[PDB]
Amino acid sequence: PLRVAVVCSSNQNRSMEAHNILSKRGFSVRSFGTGTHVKLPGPAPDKPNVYDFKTTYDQMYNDLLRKDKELYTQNGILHMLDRNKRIKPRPERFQNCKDLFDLILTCEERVYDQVVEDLNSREQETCQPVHVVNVDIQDNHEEATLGAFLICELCQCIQHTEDMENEIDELLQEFEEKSGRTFLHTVCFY
Amino acid sequence: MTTSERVVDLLNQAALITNDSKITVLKQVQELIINKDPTLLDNFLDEIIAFQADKSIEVRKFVIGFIEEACKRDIELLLKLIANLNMLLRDENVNVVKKAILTMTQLYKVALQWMVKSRVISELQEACWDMVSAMAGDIILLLDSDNDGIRTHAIKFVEGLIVTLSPRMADSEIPRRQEHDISLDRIPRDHPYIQYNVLWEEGKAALEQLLKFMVHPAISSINLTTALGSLANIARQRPMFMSEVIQAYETLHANLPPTLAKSQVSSVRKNLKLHLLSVLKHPASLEFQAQITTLLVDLGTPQAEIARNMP
């Protein structure tokens, strides 16, 4: 098969939209964020809502309907938190993960940098490679949904190859030319 | 029911299972004879190893892993097992080959430590070492493999060979995990069989092979980023090599490989930036600071980021 990780910054939107699609279509998948904090959209783009990764989805749900029941229903954040609850109790920091993956996919170049920086700085024990791929997905419901379906077609495509390492780059190129989107690609080592 | 009985039963079972599930049962046998009671390892050795012939890729990968652990538990076993390993390195399946490369990455050091710690050395043990040494030679040749995965594993193997076959120096930056790893400087100049100077030359030649690889005009994106990263490690752990690494960076930045696709070019070049910054922080980079800085700036590195990575 293919053990996949999906990674973005807050482990809320894009990365959970992909978690959800991959999980329901039979992939073994985990999702994480890399950002310093968990950020939910707030009253104004300059003042988001900020949490620690220890914080439950359910918790954020009530911290938010304590703020403005109305603002978080209309902007879909409450429905998202409820959807995330059903997958996983709390968001997770990539830098604290200890499990191994075959393929880590990132949803923003900045995160790709954080994943690379993190994996390059760890104790290398084994030299087992893990492939890291980026696709920039804007942070909104629509793009996140679209980006999850694209990530799913990608993994489904990678899973049909006979030899992943030998042909992943040809597939990513096929995918850039079909999708109009660029796919950065690198390897880190365990 | 003892361990030996609990093992005979697990094997009778494994001899009858017709699929990959048999690996579970094999992994349990592994734990029981390598960890929970090594006195039984010899009794059941031939019988685990015979699984090397199984048609299943995964069963074959499990056998290489078992070899790796048996040899860490009792390095003398390498007298027999090195043939099996070299043959599994020549497996028709790329995933078995790649596992073989990773196991050699571990065992080479271990075997060399055993040759060095050994006072008197039998002809057989000498031959065993020649085997290990030539298998390292084979894996170096795997840099010309036509498979991108084999190449990447070959690079990592070659990377560790260069670190192992060169001396730790006062300004070497050494990772916690590899603290107790043999290195050239730990090898007595007057050893009865291991020749300090033959080894020093074999590391130099290994590093020459890698530098040649970097300049293949058909080099793949992933192979190049891997090779870039291995040179950053070598450079930090073995700063007598700083000058060659910087020159390899220089060469790449004049001569960008023209089969790379646009995004591949971007991927590789984001790593070149990262490895230049990581090397700049090393004290032994002093001489070449402006040569590195020219390179970094040319790739659009901003100066708050350049300046965060001085030593």
Image: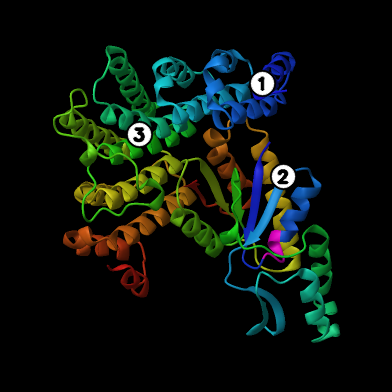
Which dot, 2 or 3, sits closer to the camera? 3
Residue B17 is situated, as x and y percent measured from the top left of the image, at 74, 17
**Classed neighbour count for the residue bearing mark 1: other residues with Cα under 10 Å, few (<14), some (14–19), many (≥20):** many
Which chain is indicated by disc 1? Answer: B
Q: Earlier in the sequence, mark 1 or mark 3?
A: 1
Residue A53 in view of the camera: yes
Disc 3: CA contacts within 10 A as few (<14), some (14-19) or many (>=20): some
User: Are the residues flagged by discs 1 and 2 from a single subunit?
Assistant: no
Residue, disc 2: A28
Query: x%, y% of residue A57?
Result: 77, 69
Residue type, mark 3 in image = Lys
Circle 1 is placed at which residue position? B7
Q: CA distance from mark 1 to mark 2?
A: 32 Å
Is B23 placed left or right of A110 in the picture?
Answer: right
Residue bearing mark 3:
B109
Q: Nearer the viewer, mark 1 or mark 3?
A: 1
For disc 2, the chain is: A
Residue at image position (55%, 35%) is A167
| In magenta stretch: residue A124 | no
Q: What span is in magenta?
A: A11-15
- From the viewer's perspective, tell me whether residue B273 is left or right of residue A140: left
How far is the residue under mark 1 from the one under mark 3? 31 Å
- Name which residue lies at 71% across and 66% down: A12
Instruction: Give the Cα separation between the discs numbered 2 and 3.
Output: 35 Å
Q: Secondary structure at mark 2?
A: strand
Crowdedness near tag 2: few (<14), some (14–19) or many (≥20) residues, C-alpha within 10 Å: some
The location of residue B108, given as percent across then percent down, is: 36, 30
